[PDB]
Image: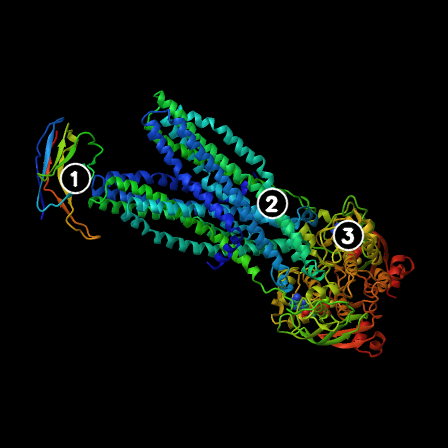
Amino acid sequence: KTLARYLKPYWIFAVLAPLFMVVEVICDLSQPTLLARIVDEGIARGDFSLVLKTGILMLIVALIGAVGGIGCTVFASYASQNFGADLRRDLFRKVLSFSISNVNRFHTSSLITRLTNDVTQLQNLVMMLLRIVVRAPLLFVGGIVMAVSINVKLSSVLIFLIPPIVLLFVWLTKKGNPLFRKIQESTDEVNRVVRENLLGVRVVRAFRREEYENENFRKANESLRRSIISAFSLIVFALPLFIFIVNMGMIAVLWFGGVLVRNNQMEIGSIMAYTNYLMQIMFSLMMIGNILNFIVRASASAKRVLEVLNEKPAIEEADNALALPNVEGSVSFENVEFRYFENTDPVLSGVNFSVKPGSLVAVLGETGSGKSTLMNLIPRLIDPERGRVEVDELDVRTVKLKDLRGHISAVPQETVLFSGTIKENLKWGREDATDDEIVEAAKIAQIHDFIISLPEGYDSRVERGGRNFSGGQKQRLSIARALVKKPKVLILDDCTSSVDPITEKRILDGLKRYTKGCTTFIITQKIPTALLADKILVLHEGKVAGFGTHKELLEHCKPYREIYESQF
Amino acid sequence: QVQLVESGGGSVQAGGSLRLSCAASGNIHHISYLGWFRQAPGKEREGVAALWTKDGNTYYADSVKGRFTVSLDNAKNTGYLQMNSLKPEDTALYYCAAADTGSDTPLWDWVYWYWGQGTQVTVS
Amino acid sequence: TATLRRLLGYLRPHTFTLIMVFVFVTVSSILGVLSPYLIGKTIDVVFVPRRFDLLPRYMLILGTIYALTSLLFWLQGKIMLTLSQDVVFRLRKELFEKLQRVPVGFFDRTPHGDIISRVINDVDNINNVLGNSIIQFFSGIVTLAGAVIMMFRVNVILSLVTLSIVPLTVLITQIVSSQTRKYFYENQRVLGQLNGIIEEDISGLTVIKLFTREEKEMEKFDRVNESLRKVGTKAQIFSGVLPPLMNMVNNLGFALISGFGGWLALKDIITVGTIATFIGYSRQFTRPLNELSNQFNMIQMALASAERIFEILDLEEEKDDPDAVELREVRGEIEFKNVWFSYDKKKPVLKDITFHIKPGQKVALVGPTGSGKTTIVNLLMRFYDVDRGQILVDGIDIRKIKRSSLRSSIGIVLQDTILFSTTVKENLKYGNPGATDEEIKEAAKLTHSDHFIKHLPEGYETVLTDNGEDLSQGQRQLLAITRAFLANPKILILDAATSNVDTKTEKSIQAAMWKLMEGKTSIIIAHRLNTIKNADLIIVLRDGEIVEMGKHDELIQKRGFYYELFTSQY
Ligand SMILES: Nc1ncnc2c1ncn2[C@@H]1O[C@H](COP(=O)(O)OP(=O)(O)OP(O)(O)=S)[C@@H](O)[C@H]1O
Ligand SMILES: Nc1ncnc2c1ncn2[C@@H]1O[C@H](COP(=O)(O)OP(=O)(O)OP(O)(O)=S)[C@@H](O)[C@H]1O
Ligand SMILES: [Mg+2]
Ligand SMILES: [Mg+2]
């Protein structure tokens, strides 16, 4: 019902397409009657004046039939493709609104199928409908009307053959639908195998597990064809069985008609015409059966499409969300307790601290402390189980998401670049950014020197994830991208992990000089880089180990001293 | 050189009968078609009766049916049309048409076609 | 027609089975014409003479005909469904197997979503040349042959008239079919483009969300989506424009044969009844002629998709030398001899890289960002080949050692950590599947991995998320380190293996790691110069050139570029 709304803006083409089919059909049904008038009345009588009179009329009705036929094809192609294009974009819009937990439910590989292959099935259903939505019932009603006009008593056996027909397409509905779902579920698995292989081919080659992955695919490929043969064997059995019942109706007509002629209830000349219009009823019945065969294939795809559309994201903006056009940078954590799963232990627990605007805080701690997790709470990527996160003395949940995220810039621990140009990727922060602004940002990130050295310059091609650049090069590009945005709150997850000490110094000292007034959070593994900060935040096993100056932490914070000793 | 003479057209009251003669003179080889058509004061060409000498099947107009009967005399070389129970609706000028096939006709090029004179048949 | 010949070659292993399909469909076609003939016969034999004593006999014959016709349809469909899916399976298999042979360079430059489209959307599109498409072609060619022999049986003169309209039908098919393939190949390439966007955007949606690029990616998607809608409508219109166009052509022929037939009747050759009969026999000829012509327009959708499938099937794949040798009794004699390399093959990355590593030596590779450290490693892994120079492992050239034995002797912990969506145990078992649970648990204990693995909901049997992102970045690196040590390679490469691993944990592993690294040659790439100072040899790289080489204390007193890098740390 919700998917029917996608055809509503294209209702003019949706009503014209079956109307043009009627125009074609009335012309195709007039073909034998007009060809009879040219031979039996034109040629037979010898009058050449009637030969051309019928001759021009037959070519004009064929022309109207052709115009009606092409028209039906044109109008059905518009509305069906426009249905799909509108649904594909509304699904991708929903997919963009999702959090990682939403993308983890509908596996990334499954979402690809749902946004393309599943829409295609619904789009094809609308295409098949628009053509024979009125052709199939009108030929069926018009056919039975012609059968009743000849003989009403003989039209009784036509009603007697409906029970095996109705039982057959009901069987195709109940058994069919879950089997077509399993094809769409098997395509998700072949997507999963090829996707993991593409995104990590170097690991496959390095460990020589190429034959293993070929077997991994073969298992998914064999399961896919087994899902296809199992759901389509259901039709290769039902259709010939239906055809048989359809042809058994002819024998039932000849047998009962034989009884009728024996009792003078029917004419011998009447049976000659009845045989033709009976096949028309049977042919039209197959078309009402064919739409059901398309309905069972589309019903599986409709469920998959609708559950994606009806899925609510993990992070949602409030109805009374305050607009945040101007921020200071007053980041605060009020007894914050976070868990990635209900079953797991608290990932973060007893987190209570405040950060003054413009101040630089060095975030430190052992692997898996919760540094990256703690930072993810600030741009509202995640929400705490207990406690609250506040920016400018305001609960992050009570503020508009685009307004909040617009003032916070991040440099993720695992840097990901996007396909296009260097210029496009740096403009990801601010689209309204000047060429002088992006150059200044890349100059602070020390990446400017490399970008200019390239033959295409700033318009140089960037591959998927930025694979065509070195580790620290794409890292320096990620720093520059965040800088462009001109944030009030900055997050740096091990900012220079893939950067040499010489370039590392140039970046850190460069940031201190031009990121004044911005509340910067810098996750680090090095004490010398941490000393640059106004205050140090130390984490150990989910809880806040300490918060204060280097001297305070060397005399009180045990894990800070533990980290200090491992370097000095 | 083949010519067709039309004779036997006069005033007959409703429900009456009248025979129409169509004499053909010339170097006729074999007549394959014999046709009769009526033309009203302001009409082009119509179709009343036709005869195909190969099978003998007669094709008549929808209004005529079991009234007019078309025939042809082989030895006399004259076409006939018997009109029975005449209604005042068929008051028009009647014409004759005949198709002849000569000895050894070209692969694609057709033979000849001949028309009649024309005689008025009035019925009231 | 070249792509058609290749596509039809996939039917060659099914030749005998396709002959049966043809044998069954010919019987189905001769029964399909015998059925209305028997209906017409029964009216003239039992109804017209009114002798209904023969009616049960004729009904039984007609019933057996229908029973045989329905059974043949089922038999045709059943054997064809399995026949068609065996072809589709082979095409999908051939695609995946090809990618495993194809070089790494392809995957980096071509969008992954487009490849995914070619494997599913394009291969599923060659189904409209198989199944019922083969049945309808077989049914068409028999009925066409059957009708044409019956036409000449009626009137030879009029048969030529119906055959003279055939070149016009073929011409309009040729015009429409060429346009159908044009817009359908374009539809499939825009589909792969759209699939590339959806795939890349989902995998990094966090970055899109963080930079509020949701709207800018929507309008980026809308450009390809509108293009797909535009070309899709064109391809759909051309696909079904032929059937109503051919009914117009049939009517031109019907009027032509009525004129020709009428002419012949006037020439004392035939009768009016013959014209009324020939129009009936022309209908049983036009029906398969229009059906086969429409089928030719329909197979263009499969032909266009076949091109995209074959495009992947003809890519210059990674091949071993004909006289390639297998490395037996590996020691670890790594050597570079005046090596030069460039990715773009215009601006050089590595310049005259020449160094020697004796077996068992723990060697450190250090330099600035984008120096060419990872490049040296990828060349030692033979992911790319040298422009000019030589790489010698155990005294044999890298090009002469088979890619199987080379990658078996050499192990790598890549700069960017790649994990899988399976159990922790299976992720560590990758590389060495013949490793006991004890060996896995002992190796994880050595790299301080076992601690967080035990904390997981299922332990080592905890199924990880896509690329194992349900762990901290450092924890992901620790798993990659464990996986590499479990693989037990004689040459091990640690390219920025502890980028996200804290200095405290890194110090704890380094001590236990040495015991399970002695007797093994290793290359350690690190920006934490303080950890690699104990190395047997320190190769200092700068702008694709080895500027300095030797031990830590020697390079420090030299006050060179290594000293400049080491002092910059504090
Ligand atoms: N796949 C690729 N395609 C094109 N250029 C590449 C590719 N991989 C690396 N490069 C370039 O090769 C040069 C050296 O890269 P690397 O070998 O990664 O350097 P590096 O010393 O390891 O630097 P890092 O990763 O930043 S510590 C740089 O100019 C990169 O842009
Ligand atoms: N998406 C996730 N799902 C489940 N657990 C997660 C997820 N992300 C992180 N964790 C766990 O949460 C804990 C803390 O996560 P992080 O914030 O990433 O750690 P960290 O202090 O940044 O450590 P590093 O990056 O390795 S120095 C670890 O025990 C992780 O395994
Ligand atoms: Mg982290
Ligand atoms: Mg690198």
The residue pinned by badge 1 equals B35
Task: Classify 10 Å Cα crowding around label 3: few (below 14), some (14-19), many (20 and above).
Answer: some
Residue situated in front as seen by the camera: A298 or A248: A248
Image quarter for residue B59? top left
The residue pinned by badge 2 equals A226
Residue situated in front as seen by the camera: C233 or C184: C184
Q: Position of residue A210 (x, y in %)?
A: 67, 58
Q: Position of residue A348 (x, y in %)?
A: 81, 50
Residue A384 visible somewhere in the drawing: yes
The mark total stands at: 3
Secondary-structure class at tag 3: helix
Asked if residue C356 lies left or right of residue C244, the reply is: right
Q: Is residue A316 above or below residue C36?
A: below
Asked if residue A165 lies left or right of residue A221, the reply is: left
Q: Which mark is residue C367?
A: none
Image quarter for residue C556? bottom right
Subunit of label 3: C
**Residue located 13% across and 27% down the image:** B14
Q: Is residue C201 above or below residue A80?
A: below
* Circles 1 and 3 on the same chain: no
Secondary-structure class at tag 1: strand
* Quadrant (top left, top right, bottom left, bottom right) of the C terminus of chain C: bottom right
Subunit of label 1: B
* Circles 3 and 2 on the same chain: no
Residue situated in front as seen by the camera: A362 or C174: C174
Q: Quadrant of ligand 1?
A: bottom right
Q: Amino acid at mark 2?
A: Arg
The residue pinned by badge 3 equals C425
Q: Amino acid at mark 3?
A: Lys
Q: CA distance from mark 1 to mark 2?
A: 71 Å
Residue positioned most to the right: A555
